[PDB]
Length: 54
Length: 19
Length: 75
Image 1 (cartoon, rainbow over the protein chains, first blue to last red):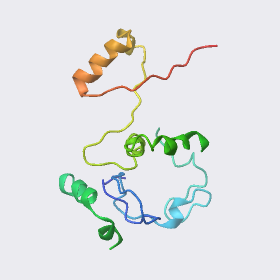
Image 2 (image 1 turned 180 degrees about the vertical axis):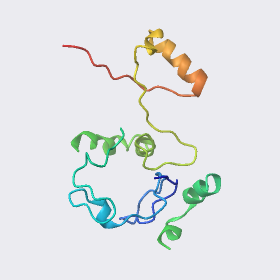
Image 3 (image 1 turned 180 degrees about the horizontal axis):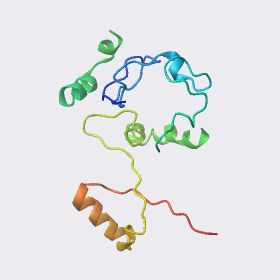
Image 4 (image 1 turned 45 degrees about the horizontal axis):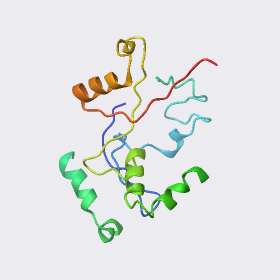
């Protein structure tokens, strides 16, 4: 997946510092953030199954 | 994107942030 | 948390001290600003022996300035 430089849209507090952070092109769903249960997107239970480089 | 985006956020005042 | 509580007490004599700390941390990044990096001295980098001569190569080639060093001795 590619990345795009930009300021993150949702700042969780008011007085926050905006910075460029290698954002995702598509805004990801809440299910795909969780590892433990693989949803209908990329069914991976553990973190090793993703195959993280670095 | 690179040049115009960075200087715009720095000069941005508190009232401009809240809006 | 109590280690950088001293920061605020130092800020009385030095107004800049908070702003310069956050620029190192990479929070309040202005357009013309830097960031902290880590160049590990591998077996190839032993070509340079001293910290003074390390200052030359970094400054001349890629316009970088070192603050300090982090050693890992066997003991």
